[PDB]
Amino acid sequence: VFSDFLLKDPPESKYKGLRLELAVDKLVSCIAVGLPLLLISLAFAQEITLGSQISCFAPTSFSWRQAAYVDSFCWAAVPLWLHKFFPYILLLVAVLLYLPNLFWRFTAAPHLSSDLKFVMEELDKCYNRDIKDIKYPIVEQYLKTKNNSYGLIIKYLICRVVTLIIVFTACIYLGYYISLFSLTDEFTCNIRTGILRNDTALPPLVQCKLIAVGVFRLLSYINLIIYVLIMPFIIYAMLVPFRKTANVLKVYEVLPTFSVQQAPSKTYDDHSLFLLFLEENVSELKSYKFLKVLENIK
Amino acid sequence: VFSDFLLKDPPESKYKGLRLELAVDKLVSCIAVGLPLLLISLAFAQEITLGSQISCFAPTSFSWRQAAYVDSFCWAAVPLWLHKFFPYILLLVAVLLYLPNLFWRFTAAPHLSSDLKFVMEELDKCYNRDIKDIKYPIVEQYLKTKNNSYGLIIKYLICRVVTLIIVFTACIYLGYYISLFSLTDEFTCNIRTGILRNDTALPPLVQCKLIAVGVFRLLSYINLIIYVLIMPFIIYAMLVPFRKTANVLKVYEVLPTFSVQQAPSKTYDDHSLFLLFLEENVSELKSYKFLKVLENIK
Image 1 (spheres, chains in turn cyan, yellow):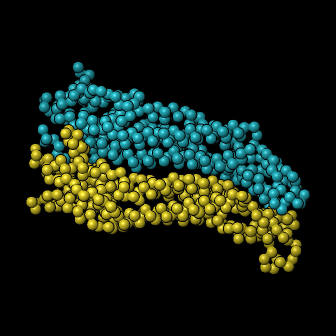
Image 2: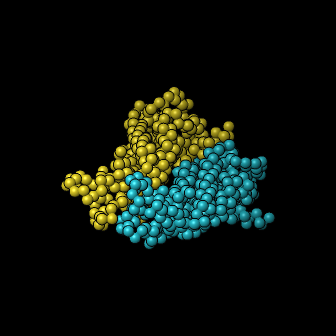
Image 3: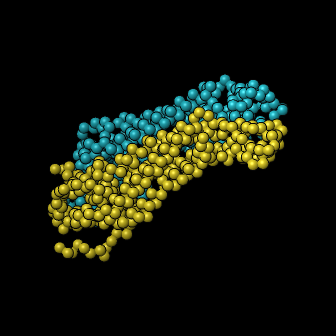
């Protein structure tokens, strides 16, 4: 009947902590954000301890400031900018990896939270009414409405694709850096450009060794290992229809007011993602344990 | 009848988190504020690691402090001030981009929040009364009153226009800097002005190379790419009437006390912006899901 649709008695803070993000996605994002931040914090601290990036052997005739000038000249411009922009690139990739979390929180979190709250409220009310009667399937209709939408799934896929693309780009950059800075970390520098061509009082070439190359190599190796370890998790999370989902509704047709589920399908609609979130958050539902034990009774 | 106008029972904290800013606007503002701040923090840290901005080759006859004096002279005054004022300009544009958020929060947030609260309260009360009757359109009148106002839409347009203008000015400045500081980062410096003209003990010219030019170029490239990526979002947000709006009222004429909407129009009035905010915040409304499932029933 049209008597259960009243909403004059809504819960205040009954749920208080609904999980709006999947556990594996949260873990992957947390790792991929924390590791670069900590590693470049370590790099900044280590070079602050060191105080320089490149060391060049200047002739004894040169004074202190002439040696400083040649050091600065050789530090500015085989691709050399890879070693110079490594921490900035790591910050950029860390910020880009943190961005999808903000996008998901700002574009899809409130609607998903409201839908989950409504669905579990309806489930609990229907279970209580049915268990009181034994001493209308609103949830089924809401899921049927969700069966044709495409917004939340598109947002989730966009977040996962952006994260995967950023991770792959970072992996490519780190591998290229590791391959390039492997033979040596020293080169020759020519202090000749400009007016310095005329005078021959300066050596034609000076040996310049790049410092902290080994530390950067170790950080690149760690980042590459972590990223190639976490990439399969992102790939698996992308395949929403093929996730190992446990049908929470499979235990709910024991009640008389629930029909047997038919036509699973669940290719790339909001039904699949919503079912995944419902399975994740079913721990809060009070009636789930009662339904499970009642099913195990028979 | 004139009996539903009582207000002796208002909710205390029923809503608790109404979204007073659009998701895309919030994301654009957050990105355009965070990126420059982090990038100039990186620039400050990097030069603190470096400790200098310009390196000049001084003659061996010069002492330490004479070289420091010529370094300072060449650092002070082809436009050179572009490289000197880059972080200050970035802070200025970041603060100017953060200003519209404060303007919107101080001038339009409370009134919009109150209007939204009143509208959803009226919607919920009318739905409950109608669903109780089946076992006066105050919202329509309030929207008709809002159909002639122009304040909130003017404030929103002012915020968007200011943000777009600041972003475009920053893009122009960054492009000009990138174009200018591309051929070289070194020049010649003349230590002659004042009493130094008479004595010939100083070289007529000295080579001075600007340091951190490549880092500034990379930061400018990143800022320009991000800003030209986010500008179309601002342009789309400016076109309020042409937004892909979903009529939340389209599901509300099922109730007998609701009339069919007519004359959409919605050119540049507060009705369009208020409808956009209502569609964004409809997730909090309890009756929206019930109306959706009832509409899907038929």
